[PDB]
Image (tube, coloured by chain):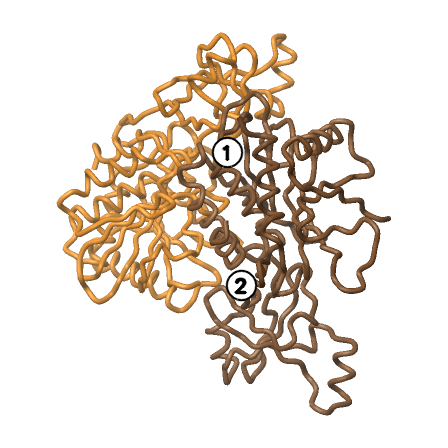
Chain colours: A brown, B orange
Amino acid sequence: MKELIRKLTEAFGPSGREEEVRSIILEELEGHIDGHRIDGLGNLIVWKGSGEKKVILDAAIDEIGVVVTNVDDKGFLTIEPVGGVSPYMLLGKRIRFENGTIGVVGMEGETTEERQENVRKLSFDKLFIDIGANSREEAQKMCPIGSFGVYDSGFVEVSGKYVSKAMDDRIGCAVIVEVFKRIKPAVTLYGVFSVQEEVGLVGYGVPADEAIAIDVTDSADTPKAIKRHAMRLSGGPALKVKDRASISSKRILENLIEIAEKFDIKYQMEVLTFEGIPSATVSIPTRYVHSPSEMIAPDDVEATVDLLIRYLGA
Amino acid sequence: MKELIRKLTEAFGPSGREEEVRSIILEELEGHIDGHRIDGLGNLIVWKGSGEKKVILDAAIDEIGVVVTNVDDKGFLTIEPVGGVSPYMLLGKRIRFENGTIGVVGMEGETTEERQENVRKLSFDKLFIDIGANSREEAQKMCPIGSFGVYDSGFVEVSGKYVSKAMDDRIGCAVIVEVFKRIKPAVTLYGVFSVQEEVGLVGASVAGYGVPADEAIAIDVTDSADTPKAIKRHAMRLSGGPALKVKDRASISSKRILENLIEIAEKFDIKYQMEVLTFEGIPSATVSIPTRYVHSPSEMIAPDDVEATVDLLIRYLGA
């Protein structure tokens, strides 16, 4: 599973430019699915099996990133966020653009007074990206306005933990792929690798009896994160307790609990403080979400795959 | 090109199930290419020649159709479209499946008023496919959920025009094949017969097919707007020649390819027409075959347009 996770987390796929991730998914699934198609919205749909019950597993394919919005007369790029990237996570980071260009993130201000004022109230308009260009025309041919970029960070093992960009939600994609690689399905099993619509803009078309979202959830097990209901690395898949869950959705949750208990699979119940298909959410606990170094525990990922295979497999 | 077009248009090739299309392309190209490769996604790449300039010709191999999404207790199939299939195009039509299974498309509603209401705003949820099965078990064995179907129509000559399913974009595939059959290339010529990698069935999706190239030319279809009550203000029409696509935000190198093609057409006395504007790694142009009734089971082309397109490409790339 390690190489699968490496390939999916390192793949280039910010919102709108996900073709490399779709291709890796399809190449990983060759020989393990009965068919596939891309729907009208760009969602990748795969399937395997023929049992009477139909179940969807869905995971988001997009990753956070940046988009180039302007180019100055000296070749420096202005950017805005794609998804939830904090400007604080970009300071001094390297960005990888779609065509392979590497850029360095800098912050405006020279005196100690102005830099400290800037960093205390850091916004994207105080950042720029240096791609080594010396003029606008040179930068425009290298990295035109509208180009997308993502963290120039990759996969690494950190004493048994896995660290990479885009664990949210490429680890969910990896779980679904691995289930398809291993499973002899007792159901008709769909995998949906879904694109995200921009916040402020306007189901996957396949009918099914159940849908299970494979997501990440924040792992609240770092220093001074002393809270009740905390999800922790190595505590197993996080099963989401939704306040307004339908009767049918609660039945799915109960099924997964009984499966995990029956087969000695670690799990934890996610309670949050403060579509039409019956649904459940199973999440991988993840530290440092939306940073270049999101961290997961491989045993949680294995336990999640095991849970889904027990529940859906022959 | 008649037999080539008949074979390619009639071949079964919906999303992910294009084995018959790729096999026909390679049999037609035997003895006319230097090599070929089928990548991990099903794209078929062929090449010929050794000139310094490298040029890609690309056409899509997938055709529109339906996919089975449910089967009821009486063996009737529920379907969703793949590509631009209109539900109105399917009423009373026959659908062909991979193993040769034929199905009949029906619509729900028994009273005349219910049927009149359903066709006023026809939706796929009111359609079903009857494959002759008498139970879910019988239907699932013949046509499992997830099976793809295509139009069960074939090639016919209609007073000198060619009519078939899947001219979009098997006619582009035919053009590329015929170019490789005849050309003595001045370039290194690559032919890419591409599967769906975007939301649309046709389109390279701006991910390099593993071939570095100096130019790429997509061979597509375009709507022929020369049927009754079409007001032809620069409309594309059958027998007007290949349609050269004007692109609004085109790069300098892309407009140069278009101008090259215009100059070839005029120097070699080849008819052409300009597909006007309606309202980035490799420079690209698009050349299209005018086609009537796109996305119906009876797409219609004029053979002289196809021949002129082949001629345009041979003369552009032969020297």
Q: Which residue is drawn at 35% across and 66% down?
A: B256
Which amino acid type is shown beneath numbered disc 1?
Ile
Whether B132 is drawn above or below B57: the answer is above
Left or right: residue A5 versus residue B155 is right
Whether B22 is drawn above or below B55: the answer is above
Along the viewing direction, whichever of A259 and B268 lies nearer the viewer: A259
Along the viewing direction, whichever of B133 and B105 lies nearer the viewer: B133
Q: Where is residue B235 in the image (x, y as percent from the top left)?
A: 43, 46
Which chain is home to disc 2? A
Q: Which residue is drawn at 33% across and 48% down?
A: B39
Which amino acid type is shown beneath numbered disc 2?
Val
Please, what secondary structure does the residue beneath circle 1 have? loop
Q: Can residue A91 be seen in this view?
A: yes
Which label belongs to residue B54? none
Q: Name the residue under label 2.
A: A156
Q: Which residue lies furthest to the right in this view?
A: A274
Q: Mark 1 points at which residue?
A: A183
Mark 2 crowd level (few <14, some 14–19, many ≥20, 10 Å Cα): some
Q: Is residue B220 visible?
A: no
- Quarter of the image for residue B173 reads top left
Whether A168 is drawn above or below A114: the answer is above
